[PDB]
Image (cartoon, rainbow, N blue to C red):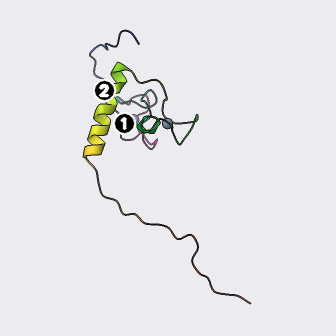
Amino acid sequence: GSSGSSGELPKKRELCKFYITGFCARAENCPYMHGDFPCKLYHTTGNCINGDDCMFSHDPLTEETRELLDKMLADDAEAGAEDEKEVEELKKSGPSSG
Ligand SMILES: [Zn+2]
Ligand SMILES: [Zn+2]
């Protein structure tokens, strides 16, 4: 990357709230980012659980994209919701059969 600049046009460079799952009514009509968008996990720590077959792009962050994360994260991180959690049972005792 050398230019960095990006003409000012009506295009959302954010992670579509649908792409996350894959059910986005508008495919090529989605003003948001789908693939190009850089992977989060791959960055959060460096390695992605998915692997080489990730649904997200693993390209090297750029002066541009970089700005995205700053927002995406800030939004999510800041706005966090509580969710139940527990430790599933490995193996509960069972009766006998004869
Ligand atoms: Zn979309
Ligand atoms: Zn990934």
Three-letter code, disc 1: Cys
25 vs 12: above or below: below
Specify the principal SS of the magenta part: loop
Work out how far the residue at label 1 is from the one at label 2, CA to CA, in angstroms: 16 Å
- Which circle marks residue 16 in the picture? 1
Stretch of the chain drawn in magenta = 12-30
Residue positioned 68% across, 87% down in the render: 96
Residue 17 location in percent, x, y?
A: 36, 41
**Would you say residue 27 sits in the magenta stretch?**
yes
Residue 46 in view (yes/no): yes
What kind of residue is marked 2?
Answer: Glu
Relative image position of residue 3 (x, y in whole percent)? 35, 9
Q: Farthest front residue?
A: 45
How many residues crowd mark 1 within 10 Å: few (<14), some (14–19), many (20+)? some
Q: Which residue is mark 2?
A: 67
Locate residue 73: give its quadrant: top left
Q: Is 9 situated left or right of 61 in this image? A: left
Q: Work out whether mark 1 precedes mark 2 in sequence or the reverse, and give the earlier one.
A: 1
Q: Quick one: label 2, few (<14), some, or many (20+) residues within 10 Å?
A: few
Q: Is the C-beta of the residue carrying label 1 under 8 Å from the nearest atom of ligand 1? A: yes
